[PDB]
Length: 326
Ligand SMILES: NC(=O)c1ccc[n+]([C@@H]2O[C@H](COP(=O)([O-])OP(=O)(O)OC[C@H]3O[C@@H](n4cnc5c(N)ncnc54)[C@H](OP(=O)(O)O)[C@@H]3O)[C@@H](O)[C@H]2O)c1
Image (tube, rainbow, N blue to C red; front, side, top):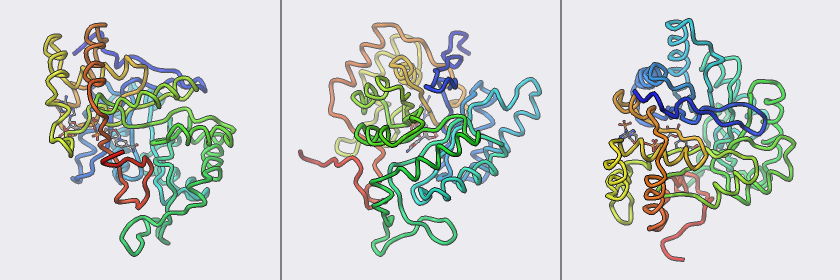
């Protein structure tokens, strides 16, 4: 346990809502039945008060039971003490489908409201009659270009959910700087959060700066970089000697140093794990010294950025227009 952990720290969103600086990522892209329940339960017991969820991962039902069981077991804690975030997927950007998606997520989570609701990608795709992702003849998402280029109808729907008090704050995920500029023009409620990939191999500094300078708070998914192993070089973030040197010299884990780096930059961090030992350890986020903070920055600044999450090939849509050359 870390008495000085920054797990007690919150940020204040531009509408006054407080968001815990550390949240637990619940994505379980590989099963099993019951694994999300155990992990979520472990996070709640370990002191997490921020849970990050999404319709896409199809496990909000297990999360709902975990929250309900945790609350039943711990009468001193109230649902209001938890910060719950979920997200609407790309095939559900039509206004009525946005509301349906939150209603569905609220049902599975066994909640009356969520603390944060996000548009998961700035990409609108067609859906099937039964509200699944419609696949085109190449097997990729079928893109609705009108709704993708002019997301106003989708955002109005988020605004209405927010005014209906079904979401205490609304935000975006994977939005770009230009995307934010376009949204600001048509938005009555400014997005409170932009959840994006942020870690030492992808510092995303220009977007992080633009958000902070504009009252949008970033939150970092993949804050540990994934163990996904950089594809053009075959190196892992968690094998990086510079990063490990800072952690080792300060008797902290590599993950804790990476999470402490993110909060120190001034944004939320959403570490994911299925492993109890790692769930427990990742809630112990240190307040980094100036030397540690700077040296991690040296690693980040000494290399070419590498984005681990790019669903180009699945979507049949290229948001970030990144190539081998150029
Ligand atoms: N488009 C979006 O909005 C989006 C995209 C991706 C993710 N997210 C959210 O953010 C979360 C993070 O995504 P991510 O899993 O790709 O990256 P991550 O949080 O940076 O961590 C990925 C992997 O690191 C391992 N790990 C965790 N703690 C560790 C520790 N102390 N020491 C060593 N290894 C550790 C874990 O493996 P084990 O599981 O085996 O323990 C975990 O799978 C997701 O769950 C999700 O809620 C959002």
